[PDB]
Image: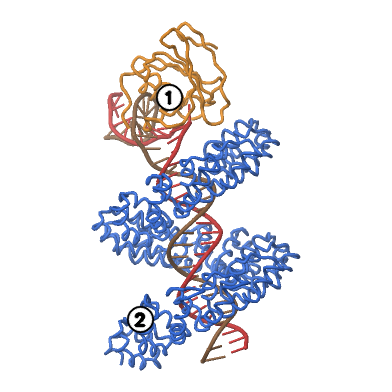
Chain colours: A orange, B blue, C brown, D red
Amino acid sequence: GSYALGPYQISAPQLPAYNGQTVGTFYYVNDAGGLEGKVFISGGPTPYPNYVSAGHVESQSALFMRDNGISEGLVFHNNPKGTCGFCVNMIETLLPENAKMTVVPPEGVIPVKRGATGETKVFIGNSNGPKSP
Amino acid sequence: DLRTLGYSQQQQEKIKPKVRSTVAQHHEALVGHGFTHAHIVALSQHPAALGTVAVKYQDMIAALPEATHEAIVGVGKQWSGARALEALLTVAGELRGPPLQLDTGQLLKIAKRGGVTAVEAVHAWRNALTGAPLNLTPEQVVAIASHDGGKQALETVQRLLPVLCQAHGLTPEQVVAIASNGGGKQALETVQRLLPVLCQAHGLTPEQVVAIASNIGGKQALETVQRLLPVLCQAHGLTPEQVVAIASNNGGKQALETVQRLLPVLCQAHGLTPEQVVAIASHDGGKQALETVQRLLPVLCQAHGLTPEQVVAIASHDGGKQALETVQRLLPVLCQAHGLTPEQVVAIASNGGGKQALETVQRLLPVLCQAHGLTPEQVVAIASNIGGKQALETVQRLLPVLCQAHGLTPEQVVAIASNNGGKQALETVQRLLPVLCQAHGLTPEQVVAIASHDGGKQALETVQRLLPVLCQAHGLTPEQVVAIASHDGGKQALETVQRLLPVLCQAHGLTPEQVVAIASNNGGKQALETVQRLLPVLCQAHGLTPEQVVAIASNGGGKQALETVQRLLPVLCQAHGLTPEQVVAIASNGGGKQALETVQRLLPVLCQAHGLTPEQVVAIASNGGGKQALESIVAQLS
DNA sequence: GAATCTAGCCTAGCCGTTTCCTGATCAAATATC
DNA sequence: GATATTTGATCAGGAAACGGCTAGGCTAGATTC
Ligand SMILES: [Zn+2]
C-alpha cells in the first residue's frame, strides 16, 4: 500500500516488465523538505567488483545514500524472486553508520533458492566500510 | 664392405645389395661437397642420381643459389631424379623471366612433385596458359603442375575450361580446384559427362558435385553415387546429404560399399545408431575404422571398460584404426606403470595422429617429470592436441633456453606449447621476443598472451608487420591491437580491421571503438563483413538502431545471430506476439541461434500445457544459456 | 620400363557453443573429540 | 558440551573447456601405355 518517508506517503509506482534485468526506483528527501526519485538498472560498471552486491539494484542505491550522505530512502524492484542471499549480508556493510533503508519486493515474490527472502526488510548500517579492490 | 666408410649395420641393411658398390664409388666426392651419411642413404632409391650430384653440383648451386642439401636430395630421390635436375639446369634460366617469374622454391616444388615431364610442359606452354582465353595466375599454374600426373591436367584444362565454363556454367576457380588434385584429368572428363545426369534425375546441386569430385580418387565416387544413391536412400533410409558427406573424402567408393554391406549388422548385433555409423564412415579411411570397430568393440568394452561412446569417439578422425589398435595394447601399461587415468588415455587418443602421441608420451614421461619439473597433468595437456609429438619434443629441447635466456616461467612455456601448432609458436617466440620487446615497446606478458592461442605464429608476424600503420594512420592504440590479435584467427581480424575501418566509420556512422569491439572475438572478420552487408537492410525494413545491431554482433558467433534474427523476426513478431526488443534481448547473450529456434519450437506447448506467459519464457531464455535451461529443468522436470 | 591413377595417415590454422571461477559476509551445521 | 569447520547464495562478465570443419604435404602399392 503505502510506506512512511518523513511526512510523505509513497505507494508502489509502475515498473517495466521483468525481462531478466532488474529495474528499480529510489525515493529520498532532499535538504529542503521535498521528495526526489531516481531510477536504477542492474549491471554496468562498478568501482567495487569484489563485492557481489555492488552491482545489484538494492546496493547501488545504498552507495548513493553514502556518496551524498543521505539518511532514509526507499527502493523498489520487479524481480519475482526477492533479494538474493548476498545482499542481506552486505547491504549493512556498504551502508554508512546509522543509515536506514527499506527494500520492498513486488507482491507475490516466491523465493526458490537458499538465502532468498520475499518480504520487506529494514537495513541499519554499521561502522565498517568496504575494502579497496 | 661398407663398415670401413662409417655406415652402421642398420644403415647397411637399408641399402640394396646391387647398389652397394655404387655407394662406395662416389662416397669421397659426395662427402667432400657437404653431404651427411643419412643424406647419402636417402639418395639411394634412385642409384643413377648418385652419379649426377657428385659430377655436377656447382652448376646446381649456380642455377639455384638458395637451394640446400635437403631439397636437392628430395628432388633426386624420386622416380625421375637425375633427369629432373638436368632439365632444371637448362630451363631455370628462361623460367625466371616473363610471363611467369618463378623463384627457387616453386621450381624445386614443381620438379620434385611433377618430374621432367611437368617441368618441360610448363616451359613449352608458358605463353598459351597465361594469355587469353585462359588468363591463369602463375600460382594457379604452379599448383596444377605440382602433382603426380602433370602434363595431362594442363592440356585437359586448356581443352575443357571454356566448354565447362560456358555450357554447364561454372566459376573459373572451380575448374582449377578440381584439376589441382591428383588425377584431375579423369575428374574433369567424368564431371563433364555426369553433371546433367546427377543434376536432373537425382536432384543434386552442382556445388555438391564439385565438392565430391575435388578429392584424390575421383571418377570413382561420382560413378558410385550414380548407382548406390537410390538403394541406400530407400532401403536403409539416409538423406542425400549424408551420402554426399560419405562420398566426399578420399576413397569414398570403399566407404559407400562398406556402409551398404555393414549397416544392418552393426545396427542390430552391436547396438549402434545409424548416425554414429555415418560419423565413423565420413572420414578418410572410413572402411578400416568400420571393420576395426566391428572386430574390437566386444573386447574393448568387456575387459578394459571403455563404454561404447568412447570407442566411437576414438574411431572417428583420420587413422582411427591405428588409434584403436594402439589403445588396445598400451592401455594396461600406461594405466599401471606411469599411473594414468583411463579417461586421460582416451582424451589423448581422440585426435589425429593419436598413435604417435601415445608412443611419445610413454617414451618421454619419465624424463619430463624427473628432469624438468613438470606434473603429469601438464604433459597430458600438451599431448592432447593435433601434433602433440612435435610439441613434446620441442618443449623438451627448448625449455631450459627459454627459461634462462629470456626469463620465462615454465607455466608460460606450458601454456604456449599447448593448442595446435605449439611447436611453431615456441620457435616464433624464441626468435621474435627480443625484436618486439625493444623496438615496438611491448611487454613480455603481452607477447606471451598473443602467442598462447591457435595460429600464434601468424598473429605475431602480422602484429610485427602491421603495428605502426594501424597505430599511426588510424589512431588506434597498441593495447587495442593486442586485444584484437589475442584471440584465434588474429591475422584475419587485423587485416579485415585495416581494410574495413574507414568504410564503416564514414559510410555507416560507427565509432572506432565499436569496430574494435566487434572484431575482438572468435571469428571477428565474419562478423565485420556480415555487419557491413546487413546493416542497411536491418535498419530500414525493420526498426532497429545501429546500437542494437552492434550489441547483437559483439559476441562469439554474431554472424549466425544476425542471419537468424533477419530470418526469424517477422514470424516470431507476428505469429507469437513478441516485441522486437525481446528478440534482440534473446539474441545478444551468447549463442543466439539455438536460443531463438528453441523458443520458436517450444513456445506453444510450454505456454499452453504448463501455463507460463510468454514473458516468463522470454526471461528464462534471455539471461544465461537458454537452450539447456528451456529443454531441461522446465520442459522436462515439469 | 616409364609414366600415371588411388587409398590411408599426419600437421597447422580457423569458426561456434557451453561450462567454470573470483572476491566477500553471516546463519546453520557435520565432524568432533 | 562445547566445539570447529564446511556449507550455498548473482539482478556479471572474462577466461577456459570441448566439440567440429578446410586446406595441404608425404608415402606405398596398383594399374595402364
Ligand atoms: Zn542482491
Left or right of B612? Residue B9 is left
Left or right of B264? Residue B466 is left
Looking at the picture, tell me which residue is in the foreground, B416 or B240: B416
Query: Which secondary structure lies at badge 2?
Result: helix
Look at mark 2 in the image and give the residue it sits on.
B39
Looking at the picture, tell me which residue is in the foreground, B479 or B24: B479
Amino acid type indicated by mark 1: Gln
- The disc placed on residue A60 is 1
Residue A37 drawn at (x, y percent)? 48, 16
- Residue furthest to the front in view is B98
Amino acid type indicated by mark 2: His
- Residue furthest to the top in view is A7
Q: Chain of mark 1?
A: A
Image quadrant of ligand 1 equals: top left
Residue at 30 percent across and 49 percent down: it is B443
Measure the C-alpha gap from mark 1 to mark 2. 74 Å
Q: Chain of mark 2?
A: B
Height in image: B219 above or below B440?
Answer: below
Looking at the picture, tell me which residue is in the foreground, B484 or B289: B484
Looking at the picture, tell me which residue is in the foreground, C17 or B334: C17
- The crowding category of the residue bearing disc 2, from other C-alpha atoms within 10 Å (few below 14, some 14 to 19, many at least 20), is some
Residue B599 drawn at (x, y percent)? 62, 39
Are labels 1 and 2 on one chain? no
Quarter of the image that includes the N terminus of chain B: bottom left
Residue B135 drawn at (x, y percent)? 59, 70
Residue at 31 percent across and 89 percent down: it is B27
- The crowding category of the residue bearing disc 1, from other C-alpha atoms within 10 Å (few below 14, some 14 to 19, many at least 20), is many
